Image (cartoon, rainbow over the protein chains, first blue to last red):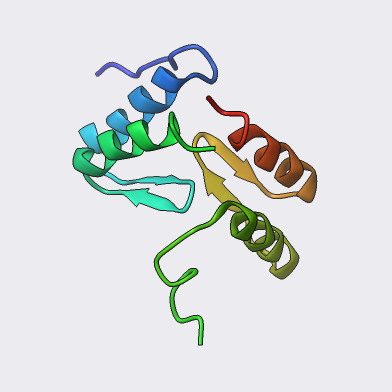
Length: 53
Length: 53
């Protein structure tokens, strides 16, 4: 009933809101060497990638 | 016998040779909000993630 029209374009919170929306419709996320099926893995992913280079 | 992608790990130099391997065998790199289908996008992706925060 309400599509999110993207956060901005590309940002840290862009990623977080995008992967959240996938989990909020009950579906997984495909990212760098990782597949997030739960928000457990999503919050671990976020703290990982903002520290990973 | 590489029955599973890099066993259960993903190193940085290993990621580069692995994503090049993917593009050279006919695959793409599905990372955070980005899909690398060319080695143009691959050199962009490597320098991106090592710069990303």
